[PDB]
Structure formats: C-alpha cells, structure tokens
Length: 257
Ligand SMILES: [Zn+2]
Image 1: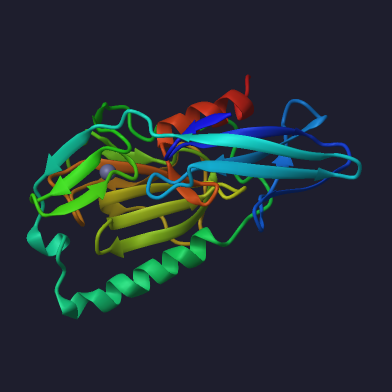
Image 2: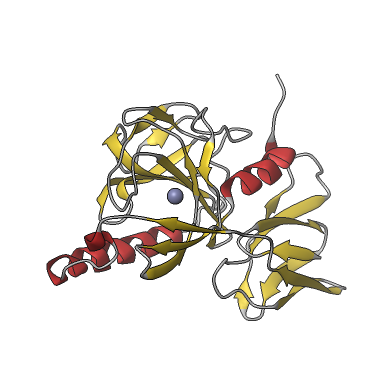
C-alpha cells in the first residue's frame, strides 16, 4: 500500500479470529465495519512532519499473522507565504506559560479514546464556501518561520455561521493563543473535528452536539493573516487532510433515507 504523508487510511481486516493490530509496539484500535459484518476497520495515519519512510503493521489472528507494508509518499504539496502579527510567531515570555498549558490540555484530550461511534452517518462540510488555503501547504511566516498547514482554510467573512461537521461531544470551546476561539468535537474512534479562529463560540465543553447544529461564528482570532475559517481533522493520532479524510469516512459510513 501507499499513503501520502498527512493522510489517513481505513484499513479493512477480517473480523473472525482477530486478536490484535500493532505498529511496532503500539496497539492500533479497531471498530466494526458498518456494512460488512465479516470485516473490521482501523484508521492508520501518517504525520505530515517526520513520518517514517516505511511502515509495517502486524495483524494477529488465532491462526494467522499478517504483515502489511505501507510506503510513505511525499505527495505534491506546494508552498505559500503568509504575513501575521510578529507576536503570533514570536510570543512574549509573559504568555508562554498559557501556551504550555493549552498544549498540555489538548494532548490530554486527543489521547482520550472513545471506543464507540458518536457520529451520525457522513460528515458535512462545516462551511458552504471555497478553499482559500489547502492542507499541507508548506508555509513561511514573515519570511522568518517555516511551518506547514495542518488543516484547510475556507473563505469566511467575520460572523459566518459555522455548523458541526458531524454529531459528537464538545471537548474544547475557548480562546487559545494560536488557534483563537477554538471548538473541538470528539466523534468517537479517535476522530476529532476542529474549528479555529472563531469570533464567537456557541457551545460548551461536554455538550452533546448534533450534526449541522450551530457551533459558532467565524472570525479572525489567534494567529491569522485575515478572517477565515480553519477546519481540521485529527484521526489515528495525527492531523490529517480533512477533506480527504471525510471522503474516505463517508464512503464507509454514509447513510441513505
Ligand atoms: Zn488553517
């Protein structure tokens, strides 16, 4: 198999007699295939930064051992230049403790695995506009700082209503330094959707949010070159191309009336 860095894969395996799926020492969780009762699924993601060049997954059965080899592809990401406030790429010392806390809080949330579906069928795009800055663009801020784009930016004037991409439970709903006013939703199975730089937040941490329900209004909070919506997906432990993830998720989990 081959996978572009920064993307996720849905691996399909036989359910009968399955014992465990591992990458080196780490167990990869599994969930049921919603249509094919003979299959299970797992999410495998490659990080954009510093992925391994090759991966060997091992699936253990009562009477089989299966090695799956996935080659990391570099993809065809392009570069872009962005102008932001100098303090948003070199923050003052008075603020770096808050940045430390916020990163520790998020790490704790993304490691909190929910082993059931909190979603309801397919994801919707949370904004009906167009892409202004695609995933994985190699960035330079102020001709000083290299970065990469860990989500996808949609055109949005300040105050555009932002709706939940799928059903889930709110895990973050507060102003953070770099992401601005941030909303993060746990959808189960380690899938989290993220909405950044909002001007207003309409939910609270712990809330059960339904697909298509209002979660806030877009804005220009945090590290921005101007007003927009930033949409992100974390799955399989990593930030992945959100619209690629949604297409792959929806092929499996979409429903009909
Ligand atoms: Zn963005």
